[PDB]
Image: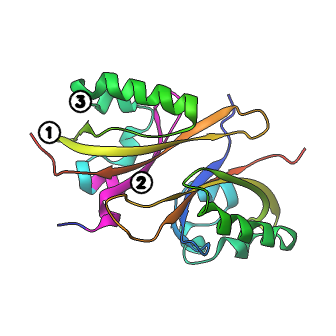
Amino acid sequence: FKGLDSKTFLSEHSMDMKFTYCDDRITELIGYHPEELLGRSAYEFYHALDSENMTKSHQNLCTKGQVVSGQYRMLAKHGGYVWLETQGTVIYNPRNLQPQCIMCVNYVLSEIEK
Amino acid sequence: VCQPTRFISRHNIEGIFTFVDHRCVATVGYQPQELLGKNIVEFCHPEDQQLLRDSFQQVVKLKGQVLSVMFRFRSKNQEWLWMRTSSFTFQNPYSDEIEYIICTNTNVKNS
């Protein structure tokens, strides 16, 4: 059993979902070091069966500014997947509503399953 | 394109830093451990402090939506830098633990 803080990790993305930042809480959860995620798209890590849903989610996030994903599976570093949900929020320029980045709060819902 | 200089932080509802991304060093010159445990208001220009307090007070009322604020933040070199902070609350929905505030802090122009 793990406490709530340990099961959340923050990430930042460019508008195409490439990682620009990840907090170190991800490592104990699913193995990655933050530095190795940078520049990779979140889409590389989504389960095949969640890919179309997560594309729709991302479109909704860009249209609306803030979304909660459905439950989805994220590929772990050493195999298997963990169930996640992610709240996404677009950060803008107020001046001109130009999007700047996506801030994600990711919370696990399972152990690694394989 | 020129990437804006920014870092993420987490705050308790009073404004205390409870998590600071190491990109703070590049943005404002402090190590994370110089921010952690301090109130954000301790870095804010006197003229902007109350605005910043009232922003933190309101963001918990806005149903998780983003509240923005621009303020002057005192860098490690004791210089006022304009920061735009975009803030929203989060709570793990499987819990009733108290909300916290997630901020993205970008150095911006006042022009």
Q: Do the residues labelled 2 and 3 touch (CB within 8 Å)?
A: no
Magenta-highlighted residues: A3-27
The chain holding disc 1 is A
* Relative height, residue A18 to residue B73 (above, below): above
Q: Which mark is residue A23?
A: 2
Q: Position of residue B86 (x, y in %)?
A: 65, 52
Nearest to the observer: residue A2 or residue B90:
B90
Amino acid beneath label 3: His
* Relative height, residue B73 to residue A65 (above, below): below
Nearest to the observer: residue B80 or residue B101:
B101
The residue singled out by tag 1 in the image is A80
Q: Quadrant of the C terminus of chain A?
A: top left
Q: In which quarter of the image is residue A51?
A: top left
The chain holding disc 2 is A
Q: Residue B39 carries which label?
A: none
Residue B4 visible somewhere in the drawing: yes
- Calculate the distance from the C-alpha at mark 2 to the C-alpha at mark 1: 21 Å
Q: Which residue is drawn at 24% across and 51% down?
A: A109
Q: Residue at x 38, y 54 (%)?
A: A9
Q: Where is residue A67 in the image (x, y as percent from the top left)?
A: 47, 39
Left or right: A38, with A89 as reference point: left
Q: Tell me, yes or no, whether dots 2 and 1 are on the same chain.
A: yes
Secondary structure category for the residue under label 3? loop
Nearest to the observer: residue B59 or residue A32:
B59
Q: Tell me, yes or no, whether dots 2 and 3 are on the same chain.
A: yes
The residue singled out by tag 3 in the image is A47
Q: Tell me, yes or no, whether dots 1 and 3 are on the same chain.
A: yes
* Relative height, residue A23 to residue A62 (above, below): below
Q: In which quarter of the image is residue A80?
A: top left
Secondary structure category for the residue under label 1? loop
Q: Residue at x 63, y 61 (%)?
A: B59
